[PDB]
Image (cartoon, rainbow, N blue to C red; front, side, top):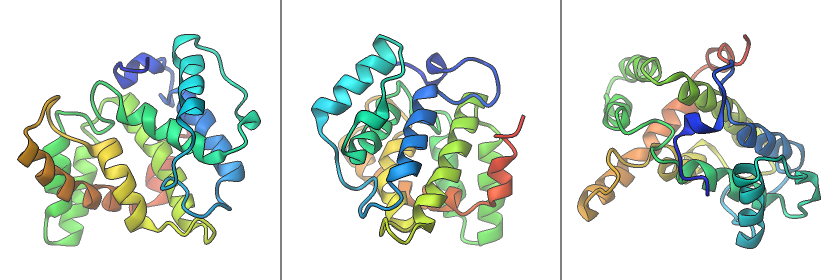
Length: 200
């Protein structure tokens, strides 16, 4: 359940963002921005599984307002993203993103980051844009006690992940050290830059 490519969960109508991602974000923005540890604290797996099956197998929109613990919604969103056949930033651009984020000169790093985003398939680009705008708001909220650095650590394994389906143990440890900076860079890009992909 939910183990397919990002594109399987959206049409080619812009913005190309899966409904599950939009509904989760809307719920989280309404009652999660006041909660400490947002995206760090895990919700009940039983709830995550039930919601996941309704969204992806039954293909209906479950009533998220009925879910008492908003952390289960954060868990659902992370679970959906993390279990895609390939990560949000794709296998093809995994290394490109890490290398871009590693350029010593900041403006040069930012330029390489923009070039990489420009290479993403549309679904990935639009979903990433939507997610970044949302996470900036999570960092911006003083109630979540989650800053850019913390969010980058949570989402590094979630959206950057690895360059291959079955990376060796050592390479995995090396990838994990490099993921956070990629997300920190992405979260720091201009709101207007990301927003342009939302207005169509």
